[PDB]
Image (cartoon, rainbow, N blue to C red; front, top):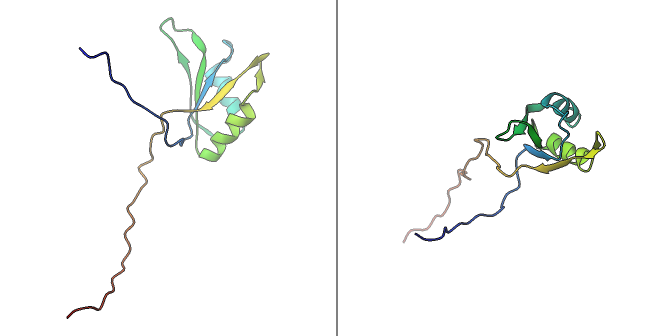
Length: 114
């Protein structure tokens, strides 16, 4: 069987979700969320765990509007929390919002007929 042909790329950095890494064990979804509350309202706040169960210093925060999300990422980008720098980067999976329509406008004109 073939090795394993793969393919991917990053074309469209959209969304609000933010990936947080290098967090303190003590830091819980509570504090994390409460903190991110600054940039804006956290629609969904939770922490990422591994097989063992203990958080690997990685969390996830979801704001309401992109604007708010961005602010946090920055205001938190390189922020020293509990004597430990946090890593807030824009999420990868940019899920849509069921909002998109094709360009359809009522325009008809062309008086030409032999």
